[PDB]
Amino acid sequence: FEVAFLLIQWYIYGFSLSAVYTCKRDPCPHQVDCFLSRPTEKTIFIIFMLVVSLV
Amino acid sequence: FEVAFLLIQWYIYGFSLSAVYTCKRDPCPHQVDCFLSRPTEKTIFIIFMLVVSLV
Ligand SMILES: CCCCCCCCCCCCCC
Ligand SMILES: CCCCCCCCCCCCCC
Ligand SMILES: CCCCCCCCCCCCCC
Ligand SMILES: CCCCCCCCCCCCCC
Ligand SMILES: CCCCCCCCCCCCCC
Ligand SMILES: CCCCCCCCCCCCCC
Ligand SMILES: CCCCCCCCCCCCCC
Ligand SMILES: CCCCCCCCCCCCCC
């Protein structure tokens, strides 16, 4: 259960977060720019919870 | 002067007007949709002034 939950997160998300996202869904016209909330503080806590599950 | 002014308008504009324009300049992000004012009434008067200059 520890290995299987680490492989789903590597496939879906990765292990960081960027500040600007580019979205191509509907009803939005062509492509839009969207901005995230605290993308640097969240990246620090993603790496803290990776080392805990590897130990 | 009548022929030279008809060839510049055929090259720049054409002889009609559409309702939705797609713009790719700066500072706009990617591509946006822009909407014109009375695009059908103006197309009727573009063709009236074409027949006058051809007669
Ligand atoms: C151990 C509990 C995890 C259950 C896994 C079931 C599959 C999860 C979906 C797989 C991702 C699909 C993305 C297209
Ligand atoms: C955008 C720059 C992010 C910098 C990431 C720094 C992460 C430090 C986390 C320390 C984890 C160590 C656990 C013992
Ligand atoms: C320069 C940006 C680096 C971002 C990742 C930093 C990770 C360093 C911390 C590793 C902790 C390992 C503890 C065993
Ligand atoms: C952007 C991703 C950076 C990942 C760097 C951290 C890797 C963790 C290595 C140390 C793990 C300690 C296991 C005991
Ligand atoms: C008879 C007066 C017309 C003057 C014509 C001078 C050239 C006009 C510009 C040509 C179009 C350039 C588009 C790139
Ligand atoms: C979008 C549909 C536009 C229909 C254009 C109709 C143009 C009629 C103009 C008549 C010109 C005749 C001059 C004698
Ligand atoms: C179906 C849309 C047709 C649009 C153009 C119509 C132009 C017809 C009028 C031509 C006038 C010619 C008078 C000599
Ligand atoms: C969308 C453009 C339609 C143009 C149709 C009208 C062409 C004009 C033909 C009649 C001209 C009369 C000259 C004497």
Image (cartoon, coloured by chain):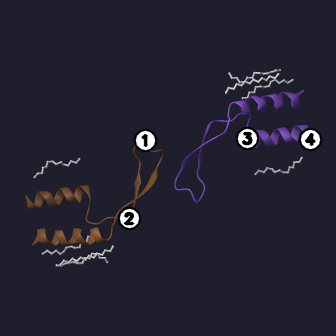
Chain colours: A brown, B purple
Q: Are marks 4 and 1 on the same chain?
A: no
Please indicate whether residue B10 sits to the left or right of residue A24 in the image. right
Q: Measuring 25% from the left and 65% from the top, which residue is drawn there?
A: A15
Task: Give the residue at mark 2.
Answer: A19
Please indicate whether residue A5 sits to the left or right of residue B41 in the image.
left
Chain bearing tag 1 is A
- The residue nearer to you, when weighing A34 against B52, is A34
Mark 3–mark 4 CB contact (< 8 Å): no
Please, which chain is the residue tagged with disc 2 on?
A: A
Report which quarter residue A51 is drawn in. Answer: bottom left
The residue positioned 73% from the left and 41% from the top of the image is B13
- Amino acid on which disc 2 is placed: Ala
**The residue at label 4 has a CB less than 8 Å from ligand 5:** yes
Alpha-carbon span between mark 1 and mark 3: 31 Å
User: Which quadrant is home to the C terminus of chain B?
Assistant: top right
User: Which residue is at a point 54% across and 48% down the rendered structure image?
Assistant: B32
Q: Amino acid at mark 1?
A: Pro
The number of numbered badges drawn on the structure is 4
Residue at image point 22% right, 60% down? A10
Q: Earlier in the sequence, mark 1 or mark 2?
A: 2
How far apart are labels 1 and 2 at the CA level? 23 Å
Q: Is residue B26 left or right of residue B41?
A: left
Amino acid type of the residue that numbered disc 3 sits on in the rendered structure = Tyr
Residue carrying label 4: B1
Return the x and y of residue A2 as percentages of the image width and height.
Answer: 9, 61
Q: Earlier in the sequence, mark 3 or mark 4?
A: 4
Rounded to the nearest angstrom, the CA distance separating label 3 from label 4 is: 18 Å
Q: Farthest right residue?
A: B1
Mark identifier at residue A27: 1
